[PDB]
Amino acid sequence: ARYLANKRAAQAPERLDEVFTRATIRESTAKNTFVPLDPEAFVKAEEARIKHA
Amino acid sequence: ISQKEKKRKMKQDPYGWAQAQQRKAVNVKRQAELQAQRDAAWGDPVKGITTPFVESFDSAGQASVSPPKVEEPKPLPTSPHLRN
Amino acid sequence: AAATKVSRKMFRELHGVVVTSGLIDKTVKVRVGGQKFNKFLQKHFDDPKQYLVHDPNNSLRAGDVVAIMPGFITSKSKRHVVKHIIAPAGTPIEERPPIPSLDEL
Amino acid sequence: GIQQITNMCSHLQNASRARLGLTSLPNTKYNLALALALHRAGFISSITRGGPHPPTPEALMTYEPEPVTSANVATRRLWVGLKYWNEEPVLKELKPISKPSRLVTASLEQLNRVARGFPAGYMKGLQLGECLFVNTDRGVLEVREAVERKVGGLVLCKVK
Amino acid sequence: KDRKHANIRRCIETFGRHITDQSLERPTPPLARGVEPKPQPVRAGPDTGSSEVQIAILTSKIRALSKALEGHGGNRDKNNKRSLRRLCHKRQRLLRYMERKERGSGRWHHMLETLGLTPATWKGQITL
RNA sequence: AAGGUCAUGGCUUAACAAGCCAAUAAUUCUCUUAGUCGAAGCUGAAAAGGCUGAUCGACCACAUUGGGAAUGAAAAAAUCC
RNA sequence: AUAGAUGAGUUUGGUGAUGGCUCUGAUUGAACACU
Ligand SMILES: [Mg+2]
Ligand SMILES: [Mg+2]
Ligand SMILES: [Mg+2]
Ligand SMILES: [Mg+2]
């Protein structure tokens, strides 16, 4: 019983009055932590070689 | 073990103690050879093992053979394409 | 009935680096991680431990990253066994003698 | 690591002491976790990932940040809007508790005691206005959000 | 100074990673478990910053300086006894990093055999 | 490799290898002091609090000092030499 | 166990600090003096 009660609370939904009152944070900033490789990493590297030469 | 147990131990069995040290002397001898062989490969912390390429620094790869002297003039790697 | 088979149990898996090799046969020193808690300062300190691991086929080289498992008693000081190589050192894995599975050992 | 959170705490103190309307922070998931909790607690006004220059002040929420890739990850920064009410900063003090030299962890019963203003462990009881942020497996939470979810974890800093 | 900057061109031409990728048989370190080789962008210029080049450049400076401290009146130069110690400790750190980073790659052995760098140069403590 | 073991371990033995632990004192030695511990006693608002180590319980040691063995299921004696 | 956290005298021509000392609280397998 002590385990179910504690596990239920840690995975409970936020309060409604907390949802309809808290300001908005764009998901582009609050969830985009992953940093992928530059898709143009190969094109840029080929242009940087020409400019450096 | 303490020093009292040392003398006491070797006093009980004088002969058995002697045999134990004869075998230890064999490994202490073999271990001294491997050290002298590893210290040689250790080298110098500044020079290590002077190679013909390191010797070519003195002339910037322009000399074909190292200076003599005892020593012997050995060929060195060169970079004749480099200018000033 | 009269056959006393080994336990054949699987213990935890630790990742570490091989510190020494070739000095003794079928044995290498592996450095693993750890952390001991100081109760007076109330903090953790790095507590790395170096064990002697069992290399049956002599397939490990110094500087190699391997995964070891305890509970495999082979000698007085050897209670760990190599599970598999994470990152080889010097030569590829396929160019070394294979590591037997725990079932084979 | 915890050193970045310690730099984020002392920097926000200096930005509020200087009465700056904006302030930048290094762009890391750890700093973003604490900033979201400060914003969720109402201590800061905004959070926006951007470049080395602050976005347009008026169009701050509708700002369109470019995707973060390896070609610009080195120049990204988190821009924080600071609050000042009644000629006083809303984020006056940010005192860290767990430091690089020692990570202080609290249990659920210690947080229950610190929430009502009673010392427990290396922490002290909370008074009127003070807040405490704990880094738990459920994210960076406020001590009263942690005891509600019944979890402990690493104590980050006490916000006066 | 003319030979100093001419030697720097020799180190970049000999140990330059842009040249050893094709000169050596197995320059890169052996792959790990599960890791597979993927193509990466080409270099926009010569390799002048790899640990091999830096360790080679430091070797040329250590010789030019250690050879001047051993010459006539070299013992009277007390200030540059720190410079030699500072060059050996800078090379010790790069050798100590490249040792674990390269995991015994053919590119690591080429540097040692060519420059004559023995374990004494990075293993323990350099006391001068 | 063999023996031993409920089993494990140079635990034991033969033959080989030169290792293993440590490098900031592992190891060893000298001097000074002390029986150890407990919400057992006293004390502080409190700290892995401080102090003590009476009466109580647990443990260690001793029986004028030093040097020893046997008996016995077991030394665990104010025994014995 | 959620009530539990306190001071005072004393350096200086004077002021603010620093820093000890002493007193205020509780106690003893206590001793001594007067009872
Ligand atoms: Mg650490
Ligand atoms: Mg002079
Ligand atoms: Mg005594
Ligand atoms: Mg005066």
Image (cartoon, coloured by chain):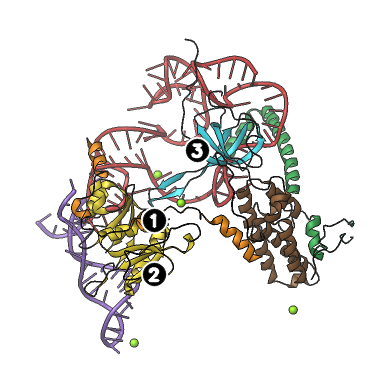
Chain colours: A orange, B green, C cyan, D yellow, E brown, F red, G purple
**Chain of the residue displaying label 1:** D
Q: Quadrant of the N terminus of chain E?
A: bottom right
Find disc 3 in the rendering and name its residue. C14
Chain identity of mark 2: D
Q: Residue F77 appears at what percent x and percent y?
A: 38, 26
Q: Are marks 3 and 2 in contact (CB under 8 Å)?
A: no
Marks 1 and 3 on same chain: no
Crowd tier of the residue under label 2, counting other residues whose Cα lies within 10 Å: few below 14, some 14–19, many 20 or above: some
Q: Is residue D12 visible?
A: yes
* Badge 1 vs badge 3, beta-carbon distance below 8 Å: no
The single residue placed furthest to the top in the displayed view is C1
Q: Earlier in the sequence, mark 1 or mark 2?
A: 1
Q: Chain of mark 3?
A: C
Q: Which residue is mark 2?
A: D54
Tell me what residue is drawn at x 63 percent, y 52 percent.
E98
Q: Are marks 1 and 2 on the same chain?
A: yes
Between C11 and E70, the one lying in front of the other is C11
Query: Residue D31 falls in which quadrant of the image?
Result: bottom left
Look at label 2 and name its amino acid: Pro
Per the rendering, the mark at residue B75 is none
User: Against F69, is D125 above or below?
Assistant: below
